[PDB]
Amino acid sequence: INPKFKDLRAYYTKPSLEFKNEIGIILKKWTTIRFMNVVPDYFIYKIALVGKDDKKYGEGVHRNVDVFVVLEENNYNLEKYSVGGITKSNSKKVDHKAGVRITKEDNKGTISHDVSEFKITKEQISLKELDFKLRKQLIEKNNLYGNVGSGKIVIKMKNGGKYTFELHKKLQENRMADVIDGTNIDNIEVNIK
Ligand SMILES: [Cl-]
Ligand SMILES: [Cl-]
Ligand SMILES: [Cl-]
């Protein structure tokens, strides 16, 4: 485990929480960004509204919301804070899978291959969740951010289109708020260099 990747490895090995079929509460702005409050247990989670989420959710109550949460440190003196990951709750049952192909190349030049399948149980999924779950898998199973920490994850959609997450840096915050049709994910290709 190499220190120039220690930040990336620490972030992508955090615990995540998934809150489904919840209610979101947006209070009046009190700092430079707005938050959606979610209360699934005895804690109040503040979810930053970044990217498209700002114009998407007005002040007030928002029902049928699902959130993929990763507690992070912040400059707003908030205890339970997470960015993006908000999706609309399911309209119906979803039971879809996407095949994952991994190729890894060492600093030695050693090349490995691996495969898995990524289960999808949500009609609408955030890039935050795809990005986060996959990297965590890559770290735990393929030693991502140990020996090497660059490359890409590419989610391919059934219609043709692609979303690519560059491994050398965290997923951009504005992108943690983008959302896609889970049912339209075809397969996932990962190249670790
Ligand atoms: Cl708030
Ligand atoms: Cl609790
Ligand atoms: Cl469901």
Image (spheres, rainbow, N blue to C red):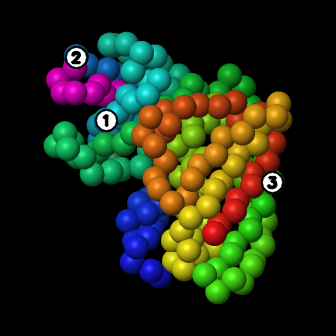
- The answer to whether residue 21 is visible is no
Q: Choose the circle earlier in sequence order: 3 or 2.
A: 2
Residue 137 image offset from top left, x and y in percent: 61, 64
- The range drawn in magenta is 29-37
Q: Amino acid at mark 3?
A: Gly
Q: Which residue is mark 3?
A: 99
For the residue marked with disc 2, what is the amino acid? Answer: Lys
Q: Residue at x 40, y 73 (%)?
A: 4
Q: Is residue 131 left or right of residue 103?
A: left
* Image coords of residue 149 (percent x, y): 54, 68
- Residue situated in front as seen by the camera: 163 or 28: 163
Quarter of the image for residue 33 reads top left
Is disc 3 placed on a helix, strand or loop?
strand
Q: Position of residue 86 (x, y in %)?
A: 49, 32
Residue highlighted by disc 1? 46
Q: Quadrant of residue 36?
A: top left
